[PDB]
Image (tube, coloured by chain):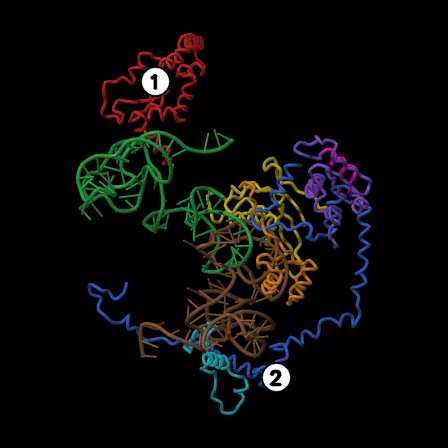
Chain colours: A orange, B cyan, C purple, D blue, E yellow, F red, G green, H brown
RNA sequence: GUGAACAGCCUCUAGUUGAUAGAAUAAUGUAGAUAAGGGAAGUCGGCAAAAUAGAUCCGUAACUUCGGGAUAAGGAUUGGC
RNA sequence: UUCAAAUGAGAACUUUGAAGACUGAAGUGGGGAAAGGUUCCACGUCAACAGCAGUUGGACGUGGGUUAGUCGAUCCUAAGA
């Protein structure tokens, strides 16, 4: 259904922008049911959401 | 503006309380004339000008 | 004066599984160990050994655990066992290899 | 082989634009890993041995308790409410009988018809229209200061 | 009749003289139409991997000769159209030339 | 192509050819006369300070050494360092008489080969 | 980062993918360009169009409220290692 | 802009995933001042509107939410009344 709210809440609780949240299309029922900070923390501990850390910005040629 | 005076805030609070559609049970009376309230207002269309 | 540094890497789990060749790993480390520029010019200063479960390296010259990790992953990809062999560190200067969380 | 591998790597990299998922935290399946293990041609004997290890949640699917409550039947009745939670509804609580509730809903549906015909944005929008424009139905467009561009 | 016959496709045949802005969408439409004409079905689905391959070089720089395979699949139940169904899938090759259509046996 | 190339190599704007350059350089008596002109007014150099190799008038007196130290003049010198060749060489290569071409090359090497070096040494 | 630069150009953190679309590319425009040879010849009228254009060195007239004019004009050079 | 999946009677536009993109830090970001005044957010729902569709909304219906001995006013004064 709708997951933008969950994505925004997860981004806020993690501390990164809303574009840096990964979700599993295979497993969506749990994330749809989850709507609390404790729920997001427990699921990210479970590893259903990744941090997808910052893209590479090399300076070697510089 | 987060700096309104108390009377201004009271006016806005009364406007917010007023802002509602008609209760459904009104139409169940006898010899009724109210169809839809014409005093309903929304922020997009009408401005109360305080 | 100079203090030697020791690093131990344990490959017990995957080698006992049977998808690892510690002797070949030791041979590769001996052949391709690089110190100060060229490869093979080691001045009898850094030695390696294998016992069948743990690979231990003792270095007196310039060396780093990050560089050891880099060489380990380079050999991992050369043997084409990446995406299946996971590298981690048990504690300071001590590392181990393990599987991943397939859990299907 | 090397040309095929470099082509596949170039296809799969996509490192430039967004990101690359870390292999240490991605999830896989032994069903998928079996083909790669076979291609590498290692000892599958000490690999499938971990399959029976998964025999822990196999019995956990059974829980009992009316065979997990006897299918989803309370949801259908609990979702019939217009609003959830325990709070006073100035529309729902006004009328008790369901027949009169349906009557009121029908009355509202009918009543909105006139505004729908008038194409108003809703029961609240009442923006009227002026019959004529002072700035569009007067003046003489002579030389000099024009009425407008 | 579930069959699998890896074909070959050149984009230059059907992307010549088209707007730079819509190179990739034109490629997608031509690919689906080519699958339609060379199979004879009604429902065609593309592969995310093929989408990655076609867009990967660039929006206005799609490579000419790309290798693809087409799989027939029987449609699921309650499909009012037909059991016919085509699914595409990419596969990379060392050299674009030197290959022709080859049917691959089911395994 | 409608750009810098045509705008710089348009038919109006042409330069001398390496063949005539080689001819005048070889001619010892022409070396002095290429610069010892009586007077000129039309050209911007007023018939003074004309670099033969670059084939241009310097328009002043002190820019001569500047252009000589410049790399472009050295580039032209390096280009002139090559063998001149002519249409006869191309004709001989394209399935024609080779004895005459070989005799001409031998005579060139025996007579005018060091002649360019001697003229350059005498001039500078 | 490119450089004199808070110019423009590409990227990072962050944010967006919203503005009706699909099939073919005829004439008549919008904004741009390009054109062999002549080079302003008609055009009220060198007006939208082009030329030098950045930096370093040389030498810079008439006139003068001697403070400017002046980057006057022109010429030589511009890479990589 | 592209593809897949899911929801959904019904998907060029809803959600997620997979790609491509741009804004390029004197931003399409992060806060605010005037002004705006419940639009913030949650839940069920789409006849009326978002010139097109909408299974979506800054739309509809019901509710939740702003905590100051230290932040500003309240204290003082200027041109003024």
Span of residues in magenta: C20-31
Looking at the image, which is closer to me, G35 or A42? A42
Q: Is residue H19 left or right of residue C76?
A: left
Report the label total.
Answer: 2
Q: Residue at label 1? A: F20
Q: Residues within 10 Å of mark 1 (few under 14, many from 20)?
A: few
Determine the image quadrant of residue H45: bottom right
Q: Is residue A38 magenta?
A: no
Q: Relative to residue B10, is residue E37 drawn left or right?
A: right
Say which of H12 and F68 sits in front: F68
Which residue is depicted at the point 67% across and 63% down?
Answer: A41
Q: Work out which quarter of the rendered image holds the N terminus of chain D and state it.
A: top right
Give x and y (percent) for residue G70.
Answer: 27, 41
> Circle 2 sits in a helix, a strand or a loop, which is it?
helix
Q: Chain of mark 2?
A: D
Residue underneath mark 2: D98
| Residue at 64% in and 67% down | A35
Q: Is residue A35 above or below residue E28?
A: below
- Residue C90 % position (x, y): 75, 49
Of residues A16 and D47, which is closer to you in this image? Answer: A16
């Amino acid at each position: 259904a709708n997951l933008r709210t969950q994505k925004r809440l997860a981004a806020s609780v993690v501390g990164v922008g809303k574009r840096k949240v990964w979700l599993d299309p295979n497993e969506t029922s749990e994330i749809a049911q989850a709507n609390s900070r404790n729920a997001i923390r427990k699921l990210v501990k479970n590893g259903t959401i990744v941090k997808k850390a910052v893209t590479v910005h090399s300076k070697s040629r510089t | 503006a987060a700096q309104k005076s108390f009377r201004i805030k009271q006016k806005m609070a009364k406007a917010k309380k007023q802002n509602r559609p008609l209760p459904q049970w009104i139409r169940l009376r006898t010899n009724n004339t109210i169809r839809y309230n014409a005093k309903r207002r929304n922020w997009r269309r009408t401005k109360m000008n305080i | 004066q100079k203090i030697a540094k020791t690093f131990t890497v344990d490959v017990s789990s995957p080698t006992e599984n049977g998808v690892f060749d510690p002797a070949s790993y030791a041979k590769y480390l001996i052949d391709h160990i690089k110190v100060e520029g060229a490869v093979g010019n080691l001045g009898n200063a850094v030695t390696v050994t294998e016992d069948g479960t743990v690979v231990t390296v003792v270095s007196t010259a310039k060396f780093s655990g990050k560089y050891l990790k880099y060489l380990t992953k380079k050999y991992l990809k050369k043997n084409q066992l990446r995406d299946w062999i996971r590298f981690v560190s048990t504690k300071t200067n001590e590392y181990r290899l393990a599987f991943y969380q397939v859990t299907p | 082989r090397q040309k095929t591998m470099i082509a596949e790597a170039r296809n799969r990299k996509s490192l430039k634009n967004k990101a690359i998922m870390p292999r240490s935290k991605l999830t896989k399946s032994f069903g998928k890993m079996e083909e790669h293990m076979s291609t590498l041609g290692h000892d599958m004997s000490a690999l499938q041995d971990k399959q029976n290890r998964a025999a822990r949640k196999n019995r956990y699917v059974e829980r009992g308790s009316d065979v997990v409550f006897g299918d989803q039947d309370a949801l259908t009745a609990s979702t019939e409410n217009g609003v959830k939670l325990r709070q006073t509804d100035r529309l729902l609580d006004g009328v008790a009988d369901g027949s009169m509730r349906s009557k009121a809903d029908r009355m509202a549906k009918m009543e909105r018809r006139e505004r729908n015909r008038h194409a108003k944005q809703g029961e609240s929008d009442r923006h009227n229209a002026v019959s004529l424009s002072k700035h569009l139905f007067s003046g003489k467009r002579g030389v000099g200061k024009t009425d407008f561009r | 009749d579930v069959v699998t016959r890896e074909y070959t496709i050149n984009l230059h045949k059907r992307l010549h003289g088209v707007s730079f802005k819509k190179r990739a969408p034109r490629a997608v439409k031509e690919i689906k139409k080519f699958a339609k004409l060379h199979m004879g079905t009604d429902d065609v689905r593309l592969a995310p991997e093929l989408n990655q391959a076609i867009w990967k070089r660039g929006v206005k720089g799609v490579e000419y000769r790309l290798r693809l395979r087409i799989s027939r699949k029987r449609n699921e139940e309650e499909d009012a159209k037909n059991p016919l169904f085509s699914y595409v899938e990419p596969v990379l090759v060392a050299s674009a030339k030197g290959l022709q259509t080859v049917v691959v046996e089911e395994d | 192509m409608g750009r810098y190339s045509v705008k710089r190599y348009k038919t109006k704007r042409r330069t001398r050819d390496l063949d005539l350059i080689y001819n005048d350089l070889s001619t010892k008596e022409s070396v002095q006369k290429l610069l010892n002109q009586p007077l000129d007014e039309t050209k911007p150099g007023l018939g003074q300070h004309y670099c033969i190799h670059c084939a241009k008038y310097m328009e002043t007196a002190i820019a001569l050494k500047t252009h000589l130290k410049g790399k472009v003049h050295k580039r032209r010198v390096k280009e002139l360092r090559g063998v001149p060749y002519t249409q006869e060489v191309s004709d001989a290569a394209a399935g024609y008489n080779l004895n005459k071409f070989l005799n001409r090359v031998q005579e060139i090497t025996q007579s005018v080969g060091p002649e360019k070096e001697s003229n350059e040494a005498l001039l500078k």
